[PDB]
Each structure stands twice: as C-alpha cells, then as structure tokens.
Length: 48
Length: 48
Image (cartoon, rainbow over all chains, first blue to last red; front, side):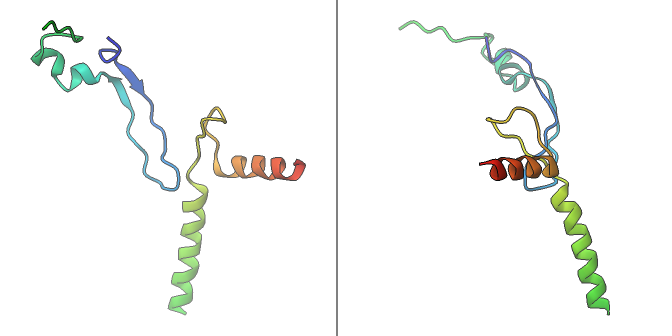
C-alpha cells in the first residue's frame, strides 16, 4: 500500500550543478507505471 | 585583448555558476544556499 501512495516530490536543485530536477506531483510507482492495472492488485499475496 | 575579454567573461560567468547552487544535508534540516552555508561553516570552524 505504501507504493500506491502518490508521493509529491518537490522541485529541488542538485548540488555542484545548475540542473534543476522537475518536481513529481502525486508520484505512485505502483500505479503511474501501470503495474496496478496489469497485476490487478495493490499488494502481493501468494500461496503455494 | 580578445583573450582577456574572454577570460574575464568566463570568470564572471563562473562566479554566478558557483554562487547559484545550494546544498541539503541530512544533519542540517532545510536547504542552505552557498553563502549562508559558507558563513555557518566559517562560524563553526572559528568557534571550535
């Protein structure tokens, strides 16, 4: 469930350079990448 | 003369390029600019 959380990443600045990383609004790796839809789940639960 | 012009312009650009970025350390909360962090380090070194 922590992966489904849309973490809001701000716009920081990398040291020793002028490259400014774009902010990431509502970043959910489990969902934005599309894995939630493919696996049709939000967690892992396997029984063997 | 052209070389001196290029050199002085490069120095002027480098001053901004060096005073532009900031820093963010885990032990020091918040983002510290170049001059503020430099002054804090000067004060800590001086008092120690």
